[PDB]
Image (cartoon, rainbow over all chains, first blue to last red; front, side, top):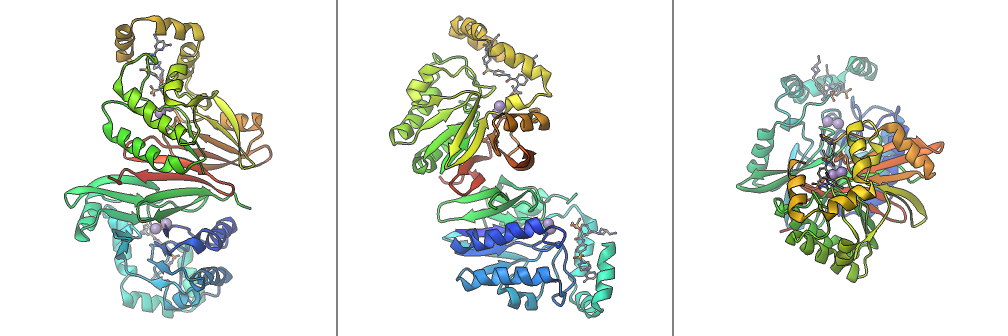
Length: 229
Length: 229
Ligand SMILES: Cc1cc(C#N)nc(N2CCN(S(=O)(=O)c3ccc(NC(=O)c4cc(CN5CC(CN)C5)ccc4N(C)S(C)(=O)=O)cc3)CC2)n1
Ligand SMILES: Cc1cc(C#N)nc(N2CCN(S(=O)(=O)c3ccc(NC(=O)c4cc(CN5CC(CN)C5)ccc4N(C)S(C)(=O)=O)cc3)CC2)n1
Ligand SMILES: [Mn+2]
Ligand SMILES: [Mn+2]
Ligand SMILES: [Mn+2]
Ligand SMILES: [Mn+2]
């Protein structure tokens, strides 16, 4: 049971989601082989030096799971691309690249956030290009926190381009893609590498949580309500 | 692990779905405590005397699960309201009423197909009234098969009315509703009986299968692709 979650959008204004996530980490995650968070863990991020107490509660909760012997990994989303090595160290999470090919019990699965598949939004992709330029990140991060805050203040999700999906799955020569970003949880069948292929999409956390569970024989998208209190 | 499925729409034209369902019965269902099929098992039904070979393949498959010690139950959908005691006997399924209150490990859950919640479609509800009138059923069933076939030949699903949902859950004084019909798989939070309540909606089988799994502590909506061949 390797688990994948994404699009939690954690924030001070939404304690119910935080509580749901902690319940998950304390419970489900402990039994897993591993946990991958495929981005948008946080609703926003202006750097690891944010003293926001939510960041340390979450880091602790995740580190307790790493310490229990369950490795956690993180791929950045569009919201939390500035999560850095200091958060990694406090949470014990390992930071991965924007695309990764896993070998899950012999099954080869491409994981990403999914925003890069959304090639029909020039708007977003121009933005992403800039905020992913390292010197623009280093610049922003060197501003005083209170100014980073002011900047962020001012600041419908386009769905994936079908071709971009195929291309990605072909580049990795894979039959399996898990991603988030779009907040449209679903299982999709398609063709890639001349064969049947599946794109499994995670949901955002608000009413419910969602995960993907990958076992030797099965791949399941699971929704769960926040009922267990 | 009590399981709920619905909206399979089984038919000769869709062998892939049949194969997916058989895989499920041979696999997942065997480990369950029980299986509830909440309607639209079949795309159509003109009476238990249909010699359609698909009907006997399915009856056998389900009966093998009943025989393995896993009780199967059926609530009619809008498509297969004419499933009768002869199919029940051949499949070993027990036929339930349009609404049922289960006690699942101390948790009280209302199950139905869901069509009765769709009170905004007069069209459909007028139709349903008539085709559920026993003498209109007895009439239709007494016509020669070939004429039933001719009749069926000529023959967007409206979503649930939010109030009808509340009313149903209030009538049964329940915090949990599982249903199908709408083909919009999801978990929904609402208020009923002055408290948090959840409506869990199953999906139709085409790309994927879906189930709801109810355990002592958890209620999960699960999508799964047809990958395991
Ligand atoms: C390195 C650096 C520099 C500067 C500066 N200087 N600022 C930062 N921020 C750090 C991150 N924070 S943040 O966490 O608060 C954040 C804020 C907004 C987004 N925006 C998008 O991701 C985004 C954006 C668009 C397109 N932009 C064009 C149009 C603007 N006119 C819209 C469309 C959709 C979106 N997403 C789908 S969406 C709908 O989820 O937001 C992302 C992160 C803000 C400051 N970083
Ligand atoms: C007892 C008896 C008598 C007679 C007669 N004599 N016929 C039968 N049939 C047995 C069942 N078969 S069936 O299995 O082939 C079947 C066919 C159609 C439906 N129709 C609906 O369920 C239905 C219908 C509408 C509304 N009707 C009004 C409008 C018609 N002008 C549309 C809207 C939506 C629908 N559903 C959501 S939908 C979109 O899924 O179909 C159901 C079962 C047909 C014969 N039974
Ligand atoms: Mn998101
Ligand atoms: Mn995103
Ligand atoms: Mn249906
Ligand atoms: Mn139906």
